[PDB]
Length: 163
Image (cartoon, rainbow, N blue to C red):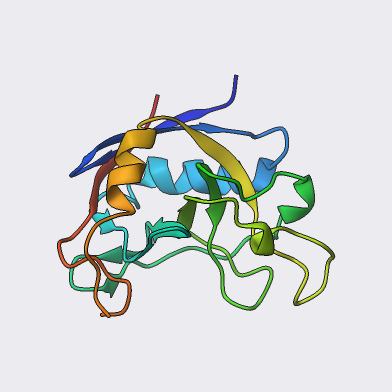
């Protein structure tokens, strides 16, 4: 019964179920970007098979879309970075997440919160893919640069919508 978002990519729809009970600020922030139209015309700019696919920040040509103020890290919510979960990207600053997200395509234990420290904070999970797992599986396997991890052919989020 979480909020639902569809990412309409150029490879098909990825449908997300979000967990606002466990990640309230993170889900609010994500839905704000969806409703603002932020993700529309962004790409998955970092694709690493066996690891994760990251997007929602850059337009084709790697032009970064402006974002709003960063949010606090909710990675202490107990949700793990397991296959098909969605989490927030960030810099080494734990409280730096804005728009960019990633979908885990493995059980990425090393991304999980252990403590509220610079090394331990981890990456905040706020939902999971409930339909279009096959689309995620296709995206993770595209050819990428060695340019490093950037898909040779753009993987575009054409529209993100709340459903």
